[PDB]
Length: 125
Ligand SMILES: *C(=O)/C=C\c1ccc(O)cc1
Image (tube, rainbow, N blue to C red):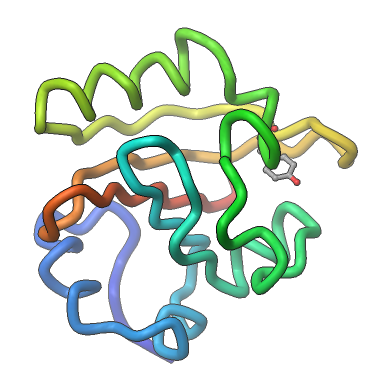
């Protein structure tokens, strides 16, 4: 298992070296979105939590297609604000409830070290 803790201050540096394969070894869910919310990476843990088959959600829009619950000021709103500002690092609890048993989670969104990419980390609470 890849030893990286949820909420780590330099997490973006650590994950910049990981391929989709290594991303599946994280102890928490990890999604990489582009500026428009399109899914570039989606690890196994995220699949476990949401029920989605990883390889099938890549290329889909997270806020429009995959996770409509999220599409709100408290989630998507924070995301679009961070994208426009070029800076993003926020942590909050949220309830995942679309076509799934309502699941409470802790979400951490942070701008990737890369150009136009952003991370969304999820773990159960
Ligand atoms: C709300 O929609 C939040 C998360 C989420 C992500 C994927 C799927 O499939 C359901 C729910």
